[PDB]
Length: 261
Ligand SMILES: *[C@@H]1O[C@H](CO)[C@@H](O)[C@H](O)[C@H]1NC(C)=O
Ligand SMILES: Nc1ncnc2[nH]cnc12
Image (tube, rainbow, N blue to C red; front, side, top):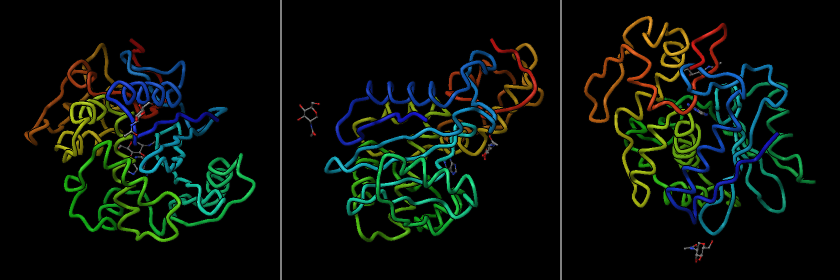
C-alpha cells in the first residue's frame, strides 16, 4: 500500500495536482486505462488500497484509505491520542474493514476505532454533514485542511463534521482523483472554498457511469450519451469519451476491455 500524502494545510494547486496525480497514479491500475484515462484497478489488485494521508489544519493528518478500485475512501485514520484512529465507514464491512483498519493503522502500534457511523454514500455523508447536498459543502483545500483539523486528533467530532470532512476529503481526494475536473475544480478554487459545482457532483455521481461509458466507449464514442452536468449544472451530454475524458482522472474500474487510449 502506498500513501499519497497531501498536506491540504499547506499546499498549492500544484501540490494538489501532484497529489492528484499521485493519487491517480497510485490508485490507477498501472495498466488499466480507457482512452488514456487511467482506470482504477479491479478490487483484486495486489495493492487494493491506497492511503491518502492528508494533513490539514494544524498539520493534523487524516489518512484516507482509499480503495484503489473505486478510490473510495474506505475510511480514514487520524492520529488520535497516539492511536491510529481509524474511522471506517460502516459499510466497509469485514475483511476490507479490517484491512482498512489495518491499512490505516499499519505503522501505528495503537489504533482505536472511531467508526464512521455511516456509510460513505454521499447521500449519507451529506445527510451526516447535514447538508442537502455536498453541493453545499464547500470544498477547498483550506476546508479540507480545516476539516482534517476538525477531525484529525479530535477526540470528538460530530458525524456532521466528519461527514463534511469526508465529503470534502472524498471529493477532494477521491473525486478529485477520479475527476480531473474535480481536481481542477479544487485547483481552480484552490485558494478558496468552493461549492462543488454540479459537474463535480455529477461527475462524482456519475463516475461509474462515466467510467463505464468511457470504458465501454468504442473509439471514443460512449455507448450512450452520458448525461452529466456541466459545471453550471446544465445538462452535459457526453457522447464521447473525449468530452468527458478531460474531466476524468480515474476511471472507475470497469472490467473487460476498453480502448486503452
Ligand atoms: C507552508 O509550507 C511552507 C514550506 O513547506 C512554509 O514556508 C509556509 O510557512 C507554510 N505555510 C503554512 C501557512 O502552513
Ligand atoms: N467514501 C467515498 N470515497 C470516495 N468516493 C465516494 N463517493 C461517495 N462516497 C465516497
